[PDB]
Image (cartoon, grey):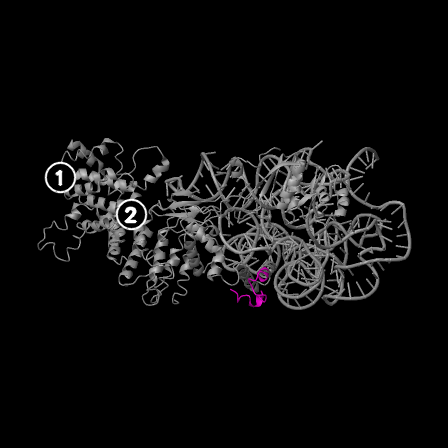
Amino acid sequence: PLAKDLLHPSPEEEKRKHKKKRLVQSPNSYFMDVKCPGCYKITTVFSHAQTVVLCVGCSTVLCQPTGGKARLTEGCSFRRKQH
Amino acid sequence: GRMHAPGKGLSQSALPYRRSVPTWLKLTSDDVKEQIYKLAKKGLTPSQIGVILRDSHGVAQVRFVTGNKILRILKSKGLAPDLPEDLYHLIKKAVAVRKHLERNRKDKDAKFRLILIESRIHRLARYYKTKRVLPPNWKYESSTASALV
Amino acid sequence: VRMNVLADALKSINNAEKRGKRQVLIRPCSKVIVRFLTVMMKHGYIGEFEIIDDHRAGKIVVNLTGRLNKCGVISPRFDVQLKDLEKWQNNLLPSRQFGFIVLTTSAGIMDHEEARRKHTGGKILGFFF
Amino acid sequence: EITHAVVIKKLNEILQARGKKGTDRAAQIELLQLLVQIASENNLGEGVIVKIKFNIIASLYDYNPNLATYMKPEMWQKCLDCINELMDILFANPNIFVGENILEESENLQNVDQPLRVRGCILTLVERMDEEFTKIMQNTDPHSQEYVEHLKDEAQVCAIIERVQRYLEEKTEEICRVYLRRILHTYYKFDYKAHQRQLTPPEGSSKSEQDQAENEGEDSAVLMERLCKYIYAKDRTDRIRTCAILCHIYHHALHSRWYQARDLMLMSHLQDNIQHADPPVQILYNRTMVQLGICAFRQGLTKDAHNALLDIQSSGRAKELLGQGLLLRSLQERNQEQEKVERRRQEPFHLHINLELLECV
RNA sequence: AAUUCUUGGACCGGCGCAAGACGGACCAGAGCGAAAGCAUUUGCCAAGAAUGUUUUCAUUAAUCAAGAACGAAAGUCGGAGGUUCGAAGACGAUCAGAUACCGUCGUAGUUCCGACCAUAAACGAUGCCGACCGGCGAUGCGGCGGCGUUAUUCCCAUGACCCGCCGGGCAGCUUCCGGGAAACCAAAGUCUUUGGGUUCCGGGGGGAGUAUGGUUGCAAAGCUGAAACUUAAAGGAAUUGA
């Protein structure tokens, strides 16, 4: 390839590229509305949390910090927030 | 590449284009300012306040929710600690290495790594002296460096 | 570290041209680069270009034609007097017919032809031929 | 040992690895236990222990990584002891034990937000316990002798939910939560329980002050549902006046009047109104509506009962009262159902209701 | 073969005892470290790269005379120790001769603690920081996504495989990128189309890393370092012969 459309890359190619090496850099992370099996109130949690996010009143604990993405505990539905 | 290492690590944050605060966030400038005040007065560095906010409360960046940087909020309110929270951490490490090295005398590696950390303390201390964050008399001296926590 | 930004911009154009690419990506854009590339374009060595605008130093995608031989920088930026344009463009440029020395004058950034025209010295940035 | 200048500052260095990966999860309750069996001085082993224990039981619940799996009987009994001791040392200590100025120390920690949302970190312990106890019951073979060995703790639970209820330093307004809890245990206690606290007729038999202590329980639904309903016409949420009334309706069935509980079921008008709540409300509605038809039959109202018990038996998917029924269409959602499923001894028998449609007709 | 050992029972075999060295096979064109270098278990102490990040500070950075830390082996002084091996030396052979190769002994040393010395083919014989310019298959660490296999049998979920993607690292294969005197090198490329930043350093071969002065070390010696005089080649890669 000599001719490549540098201005208009297709989404798959720049979804693949390292987050800094894209044309306009953008994070691979997100925020997610996540709820407990018992309670009704929802909590906003970061994709790569890196803290332990306690359910308000320490009713339980939602996430656990790891290398990359924060592991959400078993029996907690989540809906990733978008803008 | 790293200041005192042969590594060429590419691993840091990537801010999005849109600086606009998203719709789901209901925390206003004064609500997060009350939150930042509470966290700092509990005893917590501008770094640890920032992660607490984005992890638990869902505050993308405080510079967009508020109009200020966390330290400019805290130093305006007068809750900013005197000697900065990177100079602090370099001194704290340097004391921790020297305390180890005073016991384990034949630790030639700890001796070399202590020299590297102290070269980094001097180099950041003089930046803060020029920018008038420290007095011109401020000294890093291992004799009474433990007096600084 | 990146001490000269125009130096790397022109080297990356030069390698892209030699390799036979149709267009190239310049990373840290600046007024001096955009003002260099408009002088190139005005004679017609590069086509159009589009400066991609993030909230940082921008990026430039330049439409290369195959009518550029060499585009090189001169660091350091020497103080070229008007009576020295000849002895600079004698040993930098290939011939007296084609090739240009862009130099930053008080008027703006322009080639040796217009610097002679307006009766002005300045500082050499680079050359393209 | 030192005036909570080392105790509140270790409590935090042991309650920091809570939910971190390499914590082991198991050798943590030990370190939280070696702060009441090593703490043995006044407000230093005796008084501030409210807080050390709040973090001892919260971590004991967190011996289970999953929230869709049941606790084990050893740590379960340990909880039922651990919860009791807090209640007994809290009763004879008329003070708010996460703040609210009393003397000077070791309470009055108003430095942290406000002693309500962690002062009401007592019922969210015993409420989490009540939601835990259902997992023990759902995850046992119902025809086994282990099931009845496990139901022997149904009595142990209802004594603690009574003890936390007697704790009326509320601020009905917001104790409504443990009124819903209390009635959710008693609303289906049968005639032998209901009748045989007065049906030994009141003479020199059972109307003395020391025997009339369990006859409080049948006329308790009326005592408590009245509050939990007529305050939540003002208060916000839906669940703690709709679970409460359906408990009142279901309890006023299976022993008392058809006419009494039809007015309540018509008053609510859920016949056509309950459409857009959650299935864990729409299940106990079905249980109530089935108990309507059974009571009408048992009374001898043998066509208004038939005109009611049609569409349940007409459809083969009548298993909205029991465990999950038929095979496929979404494994992904069939997994969600087997923690919605109602407990065994609560289930009304199904060759009992098949023999109520096909006898009313 | 001999010098050595052995009927005051050597060598071989069994059961124990002590000593001081050393960590085989697993062990790899694998890993870590600024280089020297680093391998049985477990515990304690401080350090570190890479990755992840919608955390924080806001130019704080790159390279560096002066100055400073570490620096294999050998070697010197002091204390402890001395299993193996072994400069010196004692012989036994071979040889024209052997002051060597070979063989039996063997002091210093080899090992540990504390002071020195500061050099190696200390090598990638290749300064560091930054950007750009082909392809392929693997590999070590971190992350991310996906049929399926196997263990936790209850498999949520982790571990062992499988298929791909991203970033740092040790390397490999391949080509008319291009360069080069070539051997060859994706860097030793982007160099008469000569300019990104900066430190050290070379000028035909000898004389000579010698003399002398200075400085460091207890000593050995280290760092800095000429001249007279002699000489037309010395040398590098590759080719064809012998």
The residue marked by circle 1 belongs to what chain?
Answer: D
Q: Residue furthest front?
A: C118
- Quick one: label 1 or label 2, which is nearer the N terminus? 2
Q: Magenta part mainly helix, strand or loop?
A: loop
Relative to B16, C119 lies left or right: right
Relative to E234, C52 lies left or right: left
Question: Residue at the spot x=60%, y=44% of the render?
Answer: C29
Crowding at mark 2 (Cα within 10 Å: few <14, some 14-19, many 20+): few
- Are labels 1 and 2 assigned to the same chain? yes
Looking at the rendering, which quadrant does residue E27 occupy?
Answer: top right
Is D159 in front, or is A51?
A51
Query: Which residue, given by chain and number where applicable, does mark 2 sit on?
Result: D237
Please, what secondary structure does the residue beneath circle 1 have?
helix
Per the model, the C-alpha gap separating discs 1 and 2 is 36 Å
Q: Report x, y in % for residue B77.
A: 46, 61
Q: Report x, y in % for residue D217.
A: 19, 51
Crowding at mark 1 (Cα within 10 Å: few <14, some 14-19, many 20+): some
Query: Which residue, given by chain and number where applicable, does mark 1 sit on?
Result: D299
Say which quadrant the C terminus of chain A sits in: top left
Please, what secondary structure does the residue beneath circle 2 have?
loop
Q: Residue furthest left?
A: D203
Is E110 in front, or is A66?
A66
Q: Is residue E119 above or below residue D277?
A: below
Give the residues drawn in magenta, as a range.
B127-149
Q: Is residue B114 magenta?
A: no
Is D167 in front, or is E62?
E62
Callout 1 amino acid: Gln
Looking at the rendering, which quadrant does residue D59 occupy?
Answer: bottom left
Callout 2 amino acid: Thr
Do labels 1 and 2 touch, CB within 8 Å?
no
